[PDB]
Amino acid sequence: KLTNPGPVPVYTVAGPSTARPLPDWLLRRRKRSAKYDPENLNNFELIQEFEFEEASNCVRVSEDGNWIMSTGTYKPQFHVHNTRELSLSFSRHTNSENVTFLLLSQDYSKSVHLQCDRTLEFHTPMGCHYSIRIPRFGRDLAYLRQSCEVLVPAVGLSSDGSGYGEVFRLDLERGQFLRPWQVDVGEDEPGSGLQGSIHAGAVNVAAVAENTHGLCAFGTSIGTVEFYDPRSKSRVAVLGNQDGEITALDYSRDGLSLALGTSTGQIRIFDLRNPRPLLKKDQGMGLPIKNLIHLTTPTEERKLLSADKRIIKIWDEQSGDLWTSVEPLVDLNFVTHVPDSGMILTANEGKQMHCFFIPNLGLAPRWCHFLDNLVHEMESEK
Amino acid sequence: MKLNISHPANGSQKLIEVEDERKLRHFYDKRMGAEVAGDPLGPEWKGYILRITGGNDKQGFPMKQGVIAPNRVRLLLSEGHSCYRPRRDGERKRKSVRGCIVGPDLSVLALSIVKQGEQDIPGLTDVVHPKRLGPKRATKIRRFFSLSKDDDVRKYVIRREVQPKGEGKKPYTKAPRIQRLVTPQRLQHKRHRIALKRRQQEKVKEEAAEYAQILAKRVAEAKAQK
Amino acid sequence: GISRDSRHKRSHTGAKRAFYRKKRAFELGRQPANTRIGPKRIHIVRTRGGNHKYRALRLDSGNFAWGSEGCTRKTRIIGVVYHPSNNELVRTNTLTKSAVVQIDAAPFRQWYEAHYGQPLGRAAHGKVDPALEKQFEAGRLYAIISSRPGQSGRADGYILEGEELAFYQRKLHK
Amino acid sequence: HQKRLSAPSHWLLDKLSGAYAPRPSTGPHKLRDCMPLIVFVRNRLKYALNYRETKAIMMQRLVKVDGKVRTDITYPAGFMDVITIEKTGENFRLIYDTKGRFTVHRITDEEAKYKLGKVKRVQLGRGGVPFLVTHDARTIRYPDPLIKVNDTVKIDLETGKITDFIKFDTGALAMITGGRNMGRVGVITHRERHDGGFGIVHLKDALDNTFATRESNVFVIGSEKPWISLPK
Amino acid sequence: RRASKGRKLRYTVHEKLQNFMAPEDRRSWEEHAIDRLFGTLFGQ
Amino acid sequence: RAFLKQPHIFLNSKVRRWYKDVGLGFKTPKTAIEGHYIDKKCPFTGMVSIRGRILTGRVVSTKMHRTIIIRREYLHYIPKYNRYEKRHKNLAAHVSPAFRVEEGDMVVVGQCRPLSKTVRFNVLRVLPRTGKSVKKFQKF
Amino acid sequence: DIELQKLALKAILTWKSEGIKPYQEHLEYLLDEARFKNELTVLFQGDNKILPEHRSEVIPVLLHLLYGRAISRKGAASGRHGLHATRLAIIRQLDVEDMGSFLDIGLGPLRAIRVVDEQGVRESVFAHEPLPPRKQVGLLNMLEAVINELGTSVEPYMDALVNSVLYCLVNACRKL
RNA sequence: CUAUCAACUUUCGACGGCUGGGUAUUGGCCAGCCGUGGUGACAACGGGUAAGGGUUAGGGCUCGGAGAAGGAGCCUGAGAAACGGCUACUACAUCCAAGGAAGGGCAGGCGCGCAAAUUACCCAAUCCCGACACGGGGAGGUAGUGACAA
RNA sequence: GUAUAAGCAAUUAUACAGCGAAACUGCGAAUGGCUCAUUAAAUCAGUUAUCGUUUAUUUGAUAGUACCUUACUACAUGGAU
């Protein structure tokens, strides 16, 4: 566990130390053969077996906050950790490298994931209910909860009817594929296969509010955000012609402001009624941004940015200034905060899935109590 | 909370009964491996500092280094970890252990004296305990004794004396069979090895030459037929 | 879940048979490996007979053969440009067999100017196809991957040249 | 652990060797074409009685097969492998008969010094050197350049050197080692190619009986020249 | 047909996929504000 | 699609075409020799080799991409009738673009490594006749 | 000697400098004997190339380390792939001004030698040896690799190269 | 054996070819791309469940799917998806100082209140497994009962 | 292969020597067998092929690979249990 910046310190309590680590086999040979002397005090991990040995894809934390589900790539699996028991509860293999997973229950008792071989897989504790193939390739996943329906965006343009583009939406009380919502993606080559072209033709991100009204927002590769209203099942708005692909999409706690982002690396915080951007920030380099979420240090509101330059930037919302910047030293593919405060679980490319602790953002969560005493010890040592 | 006090340099150890959690209070919320002074413990313990290395709480559970849960927790131990030995090969077993956080619910604390003080613990630092066995391999004996090239580990090895049975016979010595000691039989082993190498290559050279002249012979006969 | 047996498919005459047995160990087929660009990540898999095969998951460099002149060099890999199997693979920047990808040209240009002498990309035996010269002036060549990155643990292949080169330029423009 | 009846019927066991029968170990000769050393000692030669007796005899260096001491009990010794026993100083060789059964022959040292082995195949080994595969699973490096497939070689058995060779020839006498006409010593008179698999030879005896055996089962012994002492 | 392997949406009910989750209606707004906002989007 | 190629012949050199004979008394056709067509399952162009059984037959459905269907007729002895009965068998074989396919001809095929679930044979020598449709019956 | 190399590089990193500061991981990975080729090809033609600003501050220590790894006899196997491919790799990935400073490091005593004067021969030079022949063999193989990888960029380095190789050739033929 | 089974497949791709992935390897085995099939009155397809070969005078002789409380995943090893282990869920059951801990099969007797063949001995021979002449073997033989007969 | 058992049993040139518990290391347990909804040329049997693959153990042969700027050197190899 280290401390990267001066003013607002970040703490990488768990995570890889090196950018290019060797084979674990050679590391074990060296450790059991030669003489070593490691920093035994501050070197540890907080959750046993928090790795995958090849890479990682996605982390989420349950609504109850007792279950951490995390997928990894080789022998493509997902581990589930009982965070009260601070260890690996189980580890289940699959047939291909997971793209995106969403939990359903407040515990881990039901999960689903869009999976690289064009599949939706449904996991119980008892096992794995039979997967459903979707016709066209997937990009992300969302779940209408007030009316149970999982919906995936897809790349390419539809088969017949129109040439708009599709978000496959199937209900769970009904079971069938209801209907792909018609979302225009852009013009394609007429001489092409059914799985689109290599340059464009993609819907990327879906995001839905679960406590406010819930406008189903979709983001398309020509930089175009659309809005569908549930209980109407039709298009409401089209806005935001941007230069980058729309890859960022999340609502606020009130249910009014949206924050979307362009793969040049430019975030725009919009209102749902004022088409002028409420806030604009171009940041980092040309590497495409990946994820963004609102969060409140319980007095003040702030915003996450995650992009694969090893850059995560916590911005302010009421001012726009940069609060904190963190360089995760390796690639990273997903970010999540614990719902309590202060800890950011980050899925990466490296072996060890790494989490950050901001003391100025919040306290240590209800299952690692001594992490505050550990930051305490770091301020003792420095 | 009894304390298993161990002096690793002198090689001695002693359990110490400890009442007065008011005296013990400085140990609380300290991770395994943290350095703590023994001056708060007792007036005899002036100038000492000691590290902690684990212990067992009530209901007898071990304390594994590297776990932050202060309560009892439930890990999954693989082969090469502490507090578990594998029943069979390749086994991963889920066991419950106590985290590194020294709480009030412990029963024994493993403590190790790292720097002494001016006073002496009576049963702890006064008593010396030797190492059980001396070094066996030749190079480690050489590093232990700082011998020169001509200084004969065969006569500088450790010896141990015992008495046998037979109603008090002569005392009897024992010597540890120095391993990495070069002998003429080792020399002849290596020499016979390289002799085997050169004999084999000599054989293949001879047979290759004879096959060369036999192929010249058979090609000459086939062309004389032609 | 994944297997290679043919019990579940239909008969040659178009019939369905129960043929209910259990998946044994010799019809095992392992999960695929999306070999992507990054630092070197290779997982070792022991297979029947105790053979080792190296599933390469993240690769940066491989070697490529400019064997027309008789050289080959270990260069980096920028990113895939076209793939005959899947446009999703072209999107997700995956390296498989027969995958055309732009590679760095600097060791090749170094070897060229060292051997023949004339600068390239800035006598009568040192001659270049003009399309290859344009690739050198841009500094990012078109090569193909022909080594199996999944079952060999290395990205190696030959540079593109001539008819295949122009064919793949036309395919990229398609 | 097959039964005595299911054991091959050409290494003989009487009606009292129990319901079981040993299986040969892994070695040069094939499973069906083997005579194990315990069955050679205590069932055919009867130089011992019991499994433990044969264990003791084979444990002391007393039975030598093909010039090398053999330790284990069930070492396979299928076909034309000389068996030198020094305490009796005898050498035994395994041939077949007209019916197709193992027949043991007694030989002294002069004819016991060499072996006659059929060539399985020939290739180039590592380093670019031709090597030669017998049916005894013996590999001879650097052979005579005329020795093709289905040749026969007289082997020194002391240095393993290629002492002589015999050529596959129509007009030569042979011995059969397989097929329904197994073990019928006679002369090769005809070869039929049948390119596409399973070439045939037509082999008659010395006394006017024609039959068709396949080249794989054919084992060349000599044109007239019976280089091994066949039993009279 | 060119489409067997899931390529067309077979609108067929699934036995195990029948009754997974009950709808829990979690919306903090009284729906009049929300559909009045859907009326008063950018367009009005 | 990608560019098709013979596996290890160097094309773009600034300084050939490989085709092997199967043997068995066969002759490679001239379209296989010089015709620039390329396919991996052709025994004269690809790396597929022919060994084992050699069979004949008559094509029935040539309307397929380089694979024919062969009706194999023979006489089945049933003991209850003590009579011979006609039985047709439906094979398949990978057809090379070297030869001129004719429907109803007499084609010799050869056993190869399994190229598909049904395709186990390669065509070697067609013999052109005037074979008719399904209504024709003959042992071949 | 690789242990002395590790201690020396630790000392140079003790010289806390902003020039060496962004490259210490590349230095230790070049030095670790199981990461040499991969660390080389991530150093050169990677995203984190040597910045030309403090290139004059980082190149000397990097080049002395490259000479150490190209001179090492411990970890090398046999054959051309044993240490010859390593030297060829280093010289192929090097640059020409870097090559000039490197050959300055490579020619120890023979950096400032003069083989020809205003007169023809310098017998006072040739009847005195500053180098053992083992080091001469190493120098000469090194320089053959340098020339073979250099090509036409030899022009600013002739007045040293020809002096070196001619001194070696004439001392050899005098030893004949 | 059957047309009270004449249409079947494309409802897990059905037949190709090309491209790759994975497999020890070939292969629609799987992922993209496009083509149109493939089977059938010479009996497809379905239905019924009643699931032999070789050794030739003869009879004899020899040989012949799914699971280890239940799904699901993983591990070693040349050879297993071992049920040997683990991991989570479910269904049981046991100990306790109530904080906690380990665990799942076969054989025998009764199965009316009235009934009837051993809870036997040894690896002695044949055979098998090991660092190995010596250790270990639930195949194998030896023994006991019988008026059911003969 | 690893013995300093604080294990026995001894002397006629003293690192060790004979026997040798425990322990580390290597091998072994792809069956001997039990239960029950069955498998209707797919298994199975003949008949081929592997130029489409794997193989511990078996026996046979088998591997020429130095120097190559450490030199004002190094020359009885390390650490763990």
Image (cartoon, coloured by chain):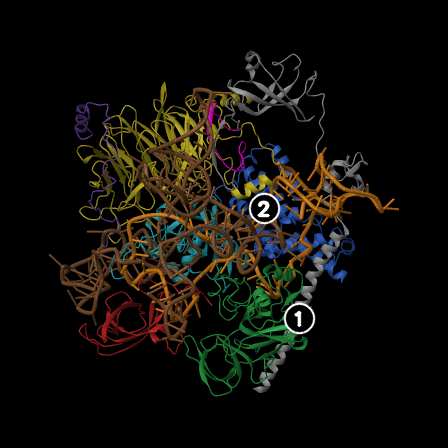
Chain colours: A yellow, C cyan, D green, E purple, F red, G blue, H brown, I orange
Q: Regarding mark 2 in the picture, which secondary structure is present there?
A: helix
Residue B74 colored in magenta in the image: yes
Q: Tag 1: Cα neighbours inside 10 Å, few (<14), some, or many (≥20)?
A: few
Q: Amino acid at mark 2?
A: Asp
Q: Quadrant of residue H126?
A: bottom right
- The chain containing the residue under callout 1 comes to D
Q: What number is the disc on residue D159?
A: 1
Q: Residue at horizontal 33%, vertical 68%?
A: F121
Q: Position of residue A65 (x, y in %)?
A: 37, 27
Left or right, residue A48 beside residue H1: right
Q: Position of residue D100 (x, y in %)?
A: 50, 75
Q: Is residue D108 above or below residue D34?
A: below
Q: Tag 2: Cα neighbours inside 10 Å, few (<14), some, or many (≥20)?
A: some
Task: State the extent of the magenta-drawn residues as a range.
Answer: B65-86
Q: Regarding mark 1 in the picture, which secondary structure is present there?
A: loop
Q: Residue at horizontal 57%, vertical 49%?
A: G96
The rendered magenta stretch, by its main secondary structure, is classed as: loop
Q: What number is the disc on residue A60?
A: none
Where is the C terminus of chain D found, in terms of image quarters?
Answer: bottom right
Residue identified by numbered label 2: G98
Tally of numbered discs = 2
Between the C-alphas of marks 1 and 2, the distance is: 62 Å
Residue C76 colored in magenta in the image: no
Residue A340 shows up from this direction: yes
Q: Position of residue A264 (x, y in %)?
A: 36, 38
Q: Nearer the viewer, mark 1 or mark 2?
A: 1
